[PDB]
Image (cartoon, rainbow, N blue to C red):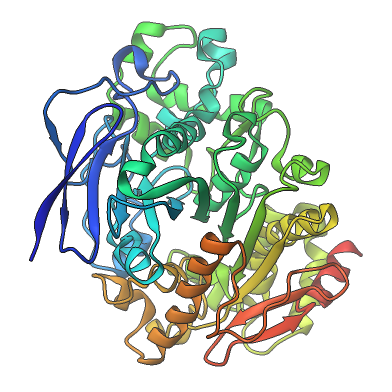
Length: 494
């Protein structure tokens, strides 16, 4: 019973599709295309249009490398891509209403991903929760995060945070236009995973983002993840420019270079997280963790968590983690934790069972993910902001169970997109999957609607506090566990 549904935005009318249970608008522009003079420059509001704009099709993704690690396990194709990528997608029960709004920032290391990916489909959230869901694209890679302040001067001030500024523009668009799609502009929750959660953590710090959301969910990511000093960022940028072949100060070459060549130059630097939001002193005045300590988000309610076996995802690329090679493992640990590596290795090697890599995978999970989660939770608890903590323990059985509860596994559970294409390849085909997704899905709904994640499906979920450190565990049997990271937190402090 699918029918076109037209809604009018400040810029113009948009044509979307509805079965009547739910409506969707795809490829709605929240900014003018960041091309030519707008390339490497802050996002600009879209030009108004006459006529009814088609919102039946997704916008192109930002230019990106293949980053096929998830894709090799999944069946996913390369994303259709263009420098003109600034589009958002809206799911709503109805254009009439003032519903709670959930705004999603995708992950992928500030280099890959898109709002258009099917696992981020908002239909189920909207239907079950009576909420409006928004997914968005932001500039990725060099075009989003290249710090050009030193190389090209003040005209490019803020260049390191362009992707963040895109996210802020989308949030501005929502404030202005969400009512037309049945959303409440005053009731907006931002949620992200990985680099998206890192993005959310930055937005809590950023003055430009203030007042644009009231609540935040950070999944497998935090303000600690990926944030760069201006100096570190300028060094990376020099390397990228070298690969690109653009001399510092050469404006014509900068605008002239094709977008794909920017992607290739970043790829040339090699694997890791070389690009990220920058403490530039404007968009980001301070480090996000410093802002949290200061009480910058004391009004904002936070749901924050991690998966039990985060780093195991990386084993798909690098199988040392499934092995017992000490020299190789030491190198990898040392890359992340530098001088502390030796002491921490001794603590983790003693704990657990199996291969050394299996025993060291928690140390990598803690350094990269758990530390940020806990610092976020602790800062909010100290300021007295409402905060809830979770650990997702449901394991995928795929590839002999070696992934466990790996990074990104929670995403279909939160969105209830388990049946969507490629998800089952990641999550396995177990029937217990659906029950776990329901409890998580409904908690995300509940948080956005009332600022409390508790629902009847769950056991009682206490706010996270320094004394008890209560953490909800999503598992076949959901439970609250108190101070689960205690042993680790003490040893890391030692």
